[PDB]
Amino acid sequence: QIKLQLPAGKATPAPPVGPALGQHGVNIMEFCKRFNAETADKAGMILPVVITVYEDKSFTFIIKTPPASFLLKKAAGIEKGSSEPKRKIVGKVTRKQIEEIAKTKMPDLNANSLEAAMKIIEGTAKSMGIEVV
RNA sequence: GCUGGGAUGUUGGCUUAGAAGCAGCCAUCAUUUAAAGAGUGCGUAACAGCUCACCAGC
Ligand SMILES: [Mg+2]
Ligand SMILES: [Mg+2]
Ligand SMILES: [Mg+2]
Ligand SMILES: [Mg+2]
Ligand SMILES: [Mg+2]
Ligand SMILES: [Mg+2]
Ligand SMILES: [Mg+2]
Ligand SMILES: [Mg+2]
Ligand SMILES: [Mg+2]
Ligand SMILES: [Mg+2]
Image 1 (tube, rainbow, N blue to C red):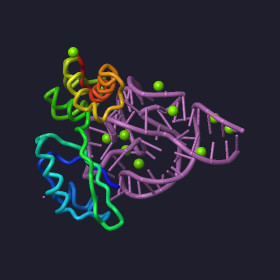
Image 2: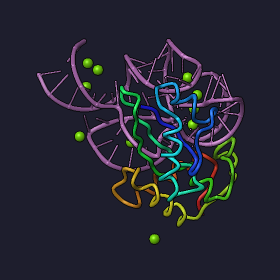
Image 3: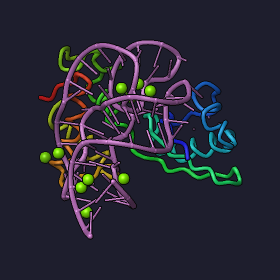
């Protein structure tokens, strides 16, 4: 069982994909087209998928919501997180934005309340030099 | 002491060919918890895997 974060509508490259699971038994081509199939509904974003390979080299994979750090980057309109979180703020997002992301990632979050969800997201923002306003 | 658990965002941000708790720098929050560090050491190219913290039962 392998896991990785592949961009929406794109796959097959050797450096990014290939070698990775391609060395566990997986047949790249089938995944590239397959992944890029459903990753059509949500394109442009980087989404993490969990590939599972059965003894017979066959496989399946679940597509999850994009990473918090990623959504956060997007929200703050930045490209990278601070090189020194807290010491240097490189961006910021509104409390409502935290709410949006928390809502977006909810299926993958284990919070029992939207409040707890936002607290989770804020923890990530605090780790990448992104402030909340 | 023994057994079982040791979870979720998440491979935290940066860096890097990679850097996924564990080269290095910064941060070290939040969730679900009985409990579980943004992780004690081993380990991998990076993962994996083993181990410790911590909790539970005996
Ligand atoms: Mg509201
Ligand atoms: Mg004891
Ligand atoms: Mg044990
Ligand atoms: Mg990382
Ligand atoms: Mg690290
Ligand atoms: Mg590392
Ligand atoms: Mg390491
Ligand atoms: Mg706690
Ligand atoms: Mg329980
Ligand atoms: Mg005990």
